[PDB]
Image (spheres, grey):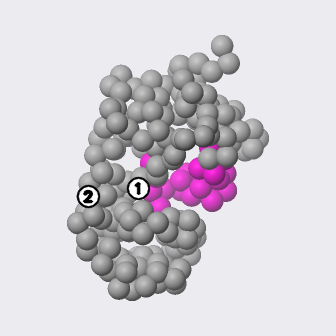
Amino acid sequence: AQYEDGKQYTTLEKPVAGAPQVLEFFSFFCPHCYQFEEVLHISDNVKKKLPEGVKMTKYHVNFMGGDLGKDLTQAWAVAMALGVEDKVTVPLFEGVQKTQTIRSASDIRDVFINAGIKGEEYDAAWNSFVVKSLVAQQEKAAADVQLRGVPAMFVNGKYQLNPQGMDTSNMDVFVQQYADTVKYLSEK
């Protein structure tokens, strides 16, 4: 058929109960993640094709970048708590990978301050238990899908996107197939 298990997607042996409908994992340290977000715009292309009533969740991962990697997961929790994901995603990616001006937790905070988040507001979130639980949620989700690498995307806690099973020549053909596959899985 057009969409096939083992081709554009795979099926989790152990489906995740109560999982987000569309769940993406990434790292700001991840070069392929930079490409996915900043050049291919995978997240946004997936958004524009999703059924009504389907939300996307995007989680950061700890396993790249050591102490800074975890600082970034905690900062991503802050972004989620404050609802400023669309203001900090580009400068965090560019700060880590393009300018490489993000070397410490303070440098991360600078991105938020520069984006208009008040210092007091950032610090209160950073030190909050709500953010600690959001970090734990991201870590738990990774365990639940038995995550091996990023970027990654899972649908209804049952299916894993398999971009290596798609065409790579036209960037844009790849991106459409990826987005079309997520929509298909969403309705499966």
* Residue corresponding to mark 1: 60
Q: Residue at x 42, y 62 (%)?
A: 80
Q: Earlier in the sequence, mark 1 or mark 2?
A: 1
Q: Disc count in the image?
A: 2
Residue type at tag 2: Ser
Residue 91 to residue 10: above or below: below
Residue tagged 2 = 133
Residue 114 x/y as whole percent: 52, 84
Residue 133 quadrant: bottom left
Identity of the residue furthest to the front in this view: 53
| Span of residues in magenta | 24-46
Picture coordinates of residue 19, whole percent (x, y): 38, 38
Q: Amino acid at mark 1?
A: His
Q: Which of labels 1 and 2 is toward the front? A: 2
Image position, residue 48 (x, y; %): 67, 46
Q: In the displayed structure, does residue 15 sit left or right of residue 155? A: left
